[PDB]
Image (cartoon, rainbow, N blue to C red; front, side, top):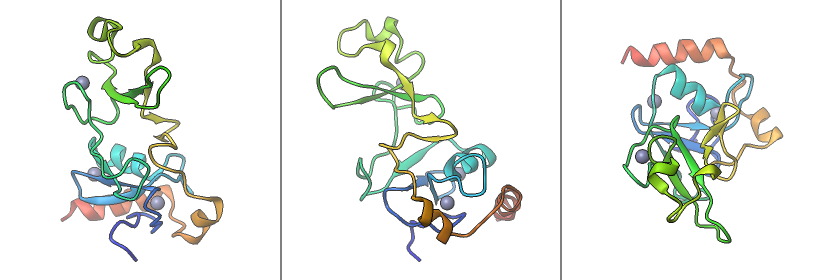
Length: 155
Ligand SMILES: [Zn+2]
Ligand SMILES: [Zn+2]
Ligand SMILES: [Zn+2]
């Protein structure tokens, strides 16, 4: 089982996993038996904010951070598409993605959208594991997560 396997379930598709900078562990973008996806569960429970994407994923090894100020809080970051072009930019909801800051010089502020929606990352950032790949993994519940998380913070 590879180093980048989800610390909850063991899914190891490079496109599906997300690295957590603070706790140095990988978590997938699938929801399993839980109501949120695994990284989001972790980021909420462990009280974490910063992540990195896999070398082999859609965006290569990228630390997700605000283009303007370098703030890395994933709960605040969102993306703005470029018009007639696919060279997206990542910015803080505030103040970096405001019409005060952007002034419509290079980016259209009204076009901002959170990186995390529906308690998980957008599929083009981190792909969602398939139906059968989620079945092959460890069928963990929300209560085992909470205990595993606590068993970790012991160390
Ligand atoms: Zn997982
Ligand atoms: Zn963490
Ligand atoms: Zn910013």
